[PDB]
Image (cartoon, rainbow, N blue to C red; front, side):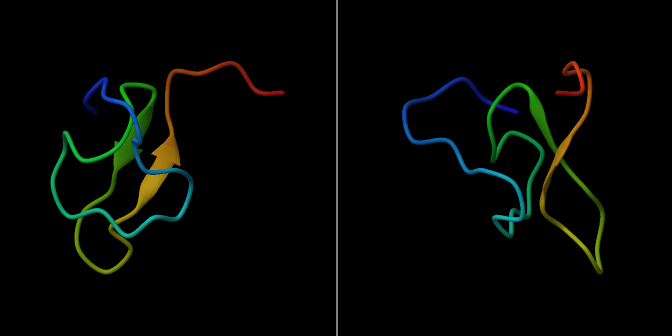
Length: 42
């Protein structure tokens, strides 16, 4: 996850690791999207 203005959100459809915010995480093939990992559950 990269810290940049306009980072992708949940279920964005990322492909790389540093594609979404630093808090989100990109999964492998099949369901490659920005998921929650490390953040506190609301």
